[PDB]
View 1 (cartoon, each protein chain N blue to C red):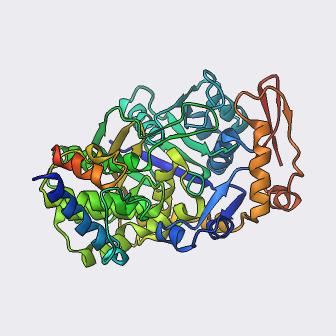
View 2: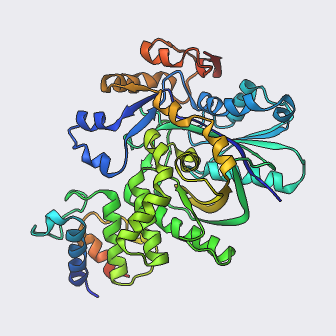
Length: 78
Length: 404
């Protein structure tokens, strides 16, 4: 239910969607885009995290995060 | 009552660019466009515009009507986000060059890529209103991507004749769900331009895809997202995104496992993507192209129901449905869409880039221009003698077209 807790869930699905990042160090400063994961898969990660936290809100409320840290915050606030 | 699409015809351009050439020229690996299921995009010449696209899409329909049936067309709706005037609808030019009756309502409809569906629904309601029994409507979605976003944005038009004898697509009357709200996902706040956010646009599409369908489900008792639809056609900015939307729907509505989702994707969704991959995103016409593609590439040995999802940035969306019979599928096949698409000129990268540079001479607001048809002689060789409309000139803002 906290930022760092959520940020761990985000890293899991990211590695799971993009397997070559499995051993890669992931900072709160990292952008899924620069990592570089395409838009369909960024959305896919977001929806996996939403369902992980069973968080049933519009998906557009998770848009606008410039890195996975900012996305952790965004999730934390819901 | 009976209502739907009596006839459907497509124009997917005279030229196209193979996206592999674009990837190579931009140092990207091919696998990214392959990943997103993009193959080719149709590309508009400077002597083509949304009007000429619309006329060329609609011409085969009109050519097959008797004089009497042609005069029964009493509404022309042009559905576009590539308009040429703040007030004059493209429908006036279309009526002129197809020779339609002067006793005809004419206007143009805008709501990004939802425009086509909105036009179709208004046409359906004209027929169902029974205000003028026997009246037909001609609905043409036409769009061009005039750059002065890029790999996915094509050019094309799809013309629908709508009547009470729906030989091609029989509408499920009242089976409609819709959903919209104001959102800045993509917009076109300047001519020959587009602004927005890829991610927000995708997430909004997915929200609408779920909510519009839920509204349909609430209205249509006992529908099942797998069992009630033999095929599904979607507004398709690119195939990979439709695959993601369908995956999300199957996961949520049916709790399907990944392997079964992928099998279901190949069976019900891939047929509609075939022509989409050959033209790119054609905006409001793209869902109609997917319907045409589903019809030509799917199995219609018995009647089938097709689910349709329309989305337009800004945004608004609709899920609706209809039935195609074996006879309707055979009529659609006589259109030869696949052969038309394969016969287009295949642009080199040098040509494509020259083409972009030259498209400036016909930007929005152009007052006078005289087109050089010999910009690309080999492209002209593919247009001449086929009975295509082209843009010849603009004179004091008046657009002049020519059959060639």
